[PDB]
Length: 97
DNA sequence: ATAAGTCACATGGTGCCGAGGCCGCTCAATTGGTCGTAGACAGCTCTAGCACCGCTTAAACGCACGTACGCGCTGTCCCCCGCGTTTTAATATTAGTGTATTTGATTTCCGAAAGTTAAAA
Image 1: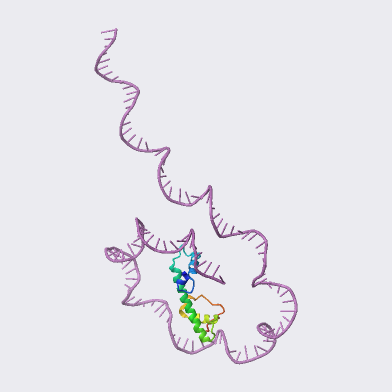
Image 2: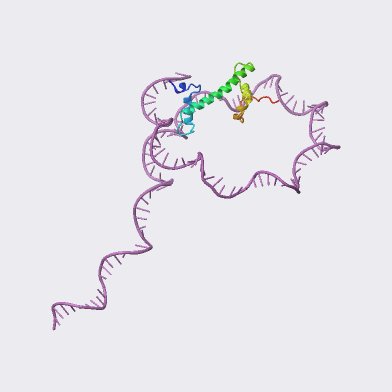
Protein backbone atom coordinates (compact mmCIF):
# COMPACT_ATOMS: atom_id res chain seq x y z
CA UNK A 1 0.00 0.00 0.00
CA UNK A 2 1.00 3.62 -0.64
CA UNK A 3 0.08 6.91 0.99
CA UNK A 4 -0.45 8.34 -2.51
CA UNK A 5 -2.71 5.34 -3.22
CA UNK A 6 -4.79 5.39 -0.03
CA UNK A 7 -5.24 9.14 -0.55
CA UNK A 8 -7.62 8.30 -3.39
CA UNK A 9 -6.36 11.39 -5.22
CA UNK A 10 -4.72 11.55 -8.63
CA UNK A 11 -1.79 13.77 -7.68
CA UNK A 12 0.63 11.87 -5.40
CA UNK A 13 0.21 13.37 -1.94
CA UNK A 14 3.66 12.06 -1.00
CA UNK A 15 5.17 14.36 -3.61
CA UNK A 16 3.09 17.22 -2.22
CA UNK A 17 4.23 16.41 1.32
CA UNK A 18 7.91 16.41 0.39
CA UNK A 19 7.42 19.55 -1.72
CA UNK A 20 6.04 21.23 1.39
CA UNK A 21 9.05 19.89 3.28
CA UNK A 22 11.64 21.43 0.95
CA UNK A 23 9.46 24.49 0.37
CA UNK A 24 10.41 25.77 3.85
CA UNK A 25 6.80 26.69 4.63
CA UNK A 26 7.30 25.44 8.19
CA UNK A 27 9.50 23.13 10.21
CA UNK A 28 6.91 20.33 10.44
CA UNK A 29 4.41 19.47 7.70
CA UNK A 30 1.01 18.37 8.98
CA UNK A 31 0.10 15.16 7.16
CA UNK A 32 -3.48 16.29 6.49
CA UNK A 33 -2.39 19.52 4.82
CA UNK A 34 -0.88 18.01 1.63
CA UNK A 35 -3.83 15.66 1.08
CA UNK A 36 -6.36 18.45 1.68
CA UNK A 37 -4.66 20.88 -0.66
CA UNK A 38 -4.12 18.09 -3.20
CA UNK A 39 -7.87 17.54 -3.20
CA UNK A 40 -8.54 21.27 -3.59
CA UNK A 41 -6.09 21.35 -6.51
CA UNK A 42 -7.75 18.28 -8.01
CA UNK A 43 -11.18 19.92 -7.84
CA UNK A 44 -9.85 23.08 -9.48
CA UNK A 45 -8.25 20.93 -12.18
CA UNK A 46 -11.61 19.19 -12.55
CA UNK A 47 -13.23 22.58 -13.13
CA UNK A 48 -10.66 23.47 -15.80
CA UNK A 49 -10.94 20.02 -17.38
CA UNK A 50 -14.73 19.74 -17.50
CA UNK A 51 -14.54 23.14 -19.17
CA UNK A 52 -11.98 21.47 -21.43
CA UNK A 53 -14.39 18.65 -22.21
CA UNK A 54 -17.31 20.91 -23.03
CA UNK A 55 -15.07 23.24 -25.06
CA UNK A 56 -13.86 20.23 -27.05
CA UNK A 57 -17.53 19.36 -27.60
CA UNK A 58 -18.42 22.91 -28.67
CA UNK A 59 -15.39 23.40 -30.94
CA UNK A 60 -15.55 19.81 -32.33
CA UNK A 61 -11.83 19.16 -31.65
CA UNK A 62 -11.73 16.13 -29.37
CA UNK A 63 -8.48 17.06 -27.58
CA UNK A 64 -8.48 20.33 -25.65
CA UNK A 65 -6.16 23.09 -26.89
CA UNK A 66 -4.78 26.27 -25.28
CA UNK A 67 -7.18 28.48 -27.25
CA UNK A 68 -10.15 26.67 -25.74
CA UNK A 69 -8.46 26.73 -22.34
CA UNK A 70 -7.97 30.50 -22.45
CA UNK A 71 -11.50 31.09 -23.71
CA UNK A 72 -13.10 28.94 -21.01
CA UNK A 73 -10.95 30.28 -18.18
CA UNK A 74 -11.66 33.86 -19.28
CA UNK A 75 -15.39 33.07 -19.46
CA UNK A 76 -15.25 31.63 -15.92
CA UNK A 77 -16.18 34.87 -14.17
CA UNK A 78 -15.55 33.79 -10.58
CA UNK A 79 -12.29 32.05 -11.48
CA UNK A 80 -10.93 35.14 -13.26
CA UNK A 81 -10.80 36.84 -9.86
CA UNK A 82 -8.32 34.15 -8.81
CA UNK A 83 -6.59 34.44 -12.21
CA UNK A 84 -7.01 38.17 -12.89
CA UNK A 85 -3.41 39.25 -13.39
CA UNK A 86 -2.85 35.76 -14.82
CA UNK A 87 -2.54 35.32 -18.59
CA UNK A 88 -2.36 32.17 -20.73
CA UNK A 89 0.18 31.33 -23.43
CA UNK A 90 -0.94 30.88 -27.06
CA UNK A 91 -4.52 31.50 -25.91
CA UNK A 92 -5.19 34.83 -27.57
CA UNK A 93 -7.93 36.83 -25.88
CA UNK A 94 -11.68 36.34 -25.68
CA UNK A 95 -13.55 38.43 -28.29
CA UNK A 96 -14.71 41.88 -27.21
CA UNK A 97 -18.04 43.09 -28.57
C1' DA B 1 59.07 53.50 107.72
C1' DT B 2 56.37 51.47 105.97
C1' DA B 3 52.77 47.43 104.69
C1' DA B 4 48.59 48.20 103.95
C1' DG B 5 45.38 51.14 102.42
C1' DT B 6 42.46 54.80 99.95
C1' DC B 7 42.48 57.48 96.15
C1' DA B 8 42.70 59.74 91.57
C1' DC B 9 44.91 59.50 87.59
C1' DA B 10 46.11 57.55 83.35
C1' DT B 11 45.62 54.43 79.96
C1' DG B 12 43.01 49.88 78.36
C1' DG B 13 39.58 47.89 75.94
C1' DT B 14 35.13 46.53 74.87
C1' DG B 15 30.98 47.53 72.78
C1' DC B 16 27.99 49.50 69.24
C1' DC B 17 27.17 52.59 64.47
C1' DG B 18 27.48 53.80 60.21
C1' DA B 19 29.83 53.28 55.25
C1' DG B 20 32.39 53.24 51.88
C1' DG B 21 34.66 49.10 49.80
C1' DC B 22 34.93 45.47 47.91
C1' DC B 23 32.40 41.07 46.30
C1' DG B 24 28.40 37.20 44.22
C1' DC B 25 25.23 35.70 41.49
C1' DT B 26 23.22 35.60 37.10
C1' DC B 27 22.35 35.70 31.73
C1' DA B 28 24.28 37.85 26.59
C1' DA B 29 26.16 36.28 22.88
C1' DT B 30 31.11 35.77 21.85
C1' DT B 31 34.09 33.09 20.28
C1' DG B 32 36.39 28.83 20.73
C1' DG B 33 36.47 24.48 18.67
C1' DT B 34 34.68 20.51 15.76
C1' DC B 35 32.26 17.53 13.18
C1' DG B 36 29.94 16.71 8.56
C1' DT B 37 28.40 18.16 4.68
C1' DA B 38 27.22 22.03 0.60
C1' DG B 39 30.08 24.15 -2.05
C1' DA B 40 33.40 24.77 -6.01
C1' DC B 41 35.37 21.95 -8.67
C1' DA B 42 37.49 18.01 -13.17
C1' DG B 43 37.75 16.28 -17.08
C1' DC B 44 33.78 16.76 -20.84
C1' DT B 45 30.93 16.15 -24.30
C1' DC B 46 27.47 17.83 -27.19
C1' DT B 47 23.07 21.70 -27.62
C1' DA B 48 20.58 24.53 -29.51
C1' DG B 49 22.91 28.80 -30.75
C1' DC B 50 23.99 31.52 -33.98
C1' DA B 51 26.03 32.60 -37.38
C1' DC B 52 27.14 32.07 -42.58
C1' DC B 53 25.79 31.81 -46.61
C1' DG B 54 22.22 31.41 -50.58
C1' DC B 55 18.27 31.43 -52.42
C1' DT B 56 12.79 33.11 -53.00
C1' DT B 57 8.69 36.24 -53.05
C1' DA B 58 5.74 37.77 -49.08
C1' DA B 59 5.45 41.80 -46.68
C1' DA B 60 6.04 46.64 -46.93
C1' DC B 61 6.88 50.91 -47.95
C1' DG B 62 5.91 54.58 -50.60
C1' DC B 63 2.71 56.44 -54.21
C1' DA B 64 -1.68 58.31 -54.94
C1' DC B 65 -6.08 59.96 -52.78
C1' DG B 66 -10.86 59.89 -50.29
C1' DT B 67 -14.10 59.46 -48.08
C1' DA B 68 -14.56 59.73 -43.46
C1' DC B 69 -13.68 62.36 -40.29
C1' DG B 70 -12.40 66.31 -35.97
C1' DC B 71 -12.66 69.81 -34.29
C1' DG B 72 -13.52 73.67 -33.02
C1' DC B 73 -18.30 75.62 -33.49
C1' DT B 74 -22.52 77.58 -31.17
C1' DG B 75 -27.10 78.40 -29.41
C1' DT B 76 -28.81 76.86 -25.01
C1' DC B 77 -29.81 74.00 -22.00
C1' DC B 78 -28.89 72.86 -17.62
C1' DC B 79 -26.74 71.87 -13.18
C1' DC B 80 -23.51 72.77 -9.42
C1' DC B 81 -23.01 75.20 -5.90
C1' DG B 82 -22.14 79.19 -2.99
C1' DC B 83 -23.89 79.96 0.23
C1' DG B 84 -27.91 80.84 3.72
C1' DT B 85 -30.19 78.52 6.51
C1' DT B 86 -32.34 75.26 10.11
C1' DT B 87 -31.73 71.25 11.40
C1' DT B 88 -29.06 67.33 13.02
C1' DA B 89 -26.53 64.43 14.33
C1' DA B 90 -21.47 64.39 15.33
C1' DT B 91 -19.16 64.99 18.69
C1' DA B 92 -16.81 63.03 23.19
C1' DT B 93 -17.54 62.46 27.17
C1' DT B 94 -18.14 57.63 31.66
C1' DA B 95 -18.82 52.38 32.38
C1' DG B 96 -18.95 47.76 34.02
C1' DT B 97 -19.83 43.92 32.42
C1' DG B 98 -18.83 40.20 29.76
C1' DT B 99 -16.34 37.84 27.38
C1' DA B 100 -11.31 38.16 25.31
C1' DT B 101 -7.07 37.45 25.88
C1' DT B 102 -4.06 34.84 28.22
C1' DT B 103 -0.38 32.54 30.49
C1' DG B 104 0.62 29.03 33.15
C1' DA B 105 1.39 23.22 33.62
C1' DT B 106 1.08 19.85 31.38
C1' DT B 107 0.01 16.14 28.06
C1' DT B 108 -0.66 14.18 24.53
C1' DC B 109 0.60 14.95 19.16
C1' DC B 110 2.84 13.67 15.40
C1' DG B 111 6.16 13.93 11.87
C1' DA B 112 11.25 14.25 11.43
C1' DA B 113 14.44 10.88 12.00
C1' DA B 114 16.06 6.07 11.57
C1' DG B 115 15.80 1.87 9.83
C1' DT B 116 13.55 -1.35 6.31
C1' DT B 117 11.88 -2.09 1.94
C1' DA B 118 8.38 -1.09 -1.63
C1' DA B 119 8.69 0.30 -6.46
C1' DA B 120 10.44 2.23 -10.64
C1' DA B 121 11.85 3.99 -15.80
